[PDB]
Length: 162
Image 1 (tube, rainbow, N blue to C red):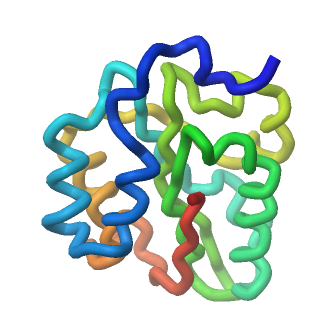
Image 2: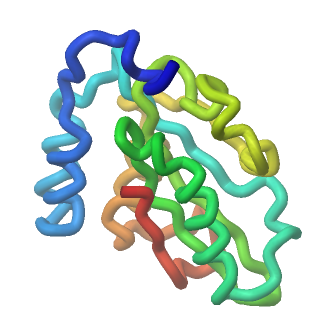
């Protein structure tokens, strides 16, 4: 009665390795190609979110703290999941968006009511690792260089769920 991704076999792809080159290297041609060659689309999955209640946001300094407060509940989760959550906009109209990774068919939150607090106010959808959009969104959320025009806010403050 611990670790939801313990029913699964050997983990092919190595999240904790990827997390180094992700920021240690030129991800655009380092982590990106090393992620898009042989991901693990049988087991890992990508989950886009855009904080479905961005009305709840009304500063900048606080939202970075808020995102992270979630991550401190999800502290027994990061051991088999990651995300690149970004705070956008400003006080006047902020938003949180980002893409998360969880190691099963589900987003991990439903795999344990340990992690079913305020998550409902955020969207969570699986997407295809050979779409067009997912590949762009990932590149933007992972490089921070992308364009973020799909948000149309501004990038202000990134956060990582490592």
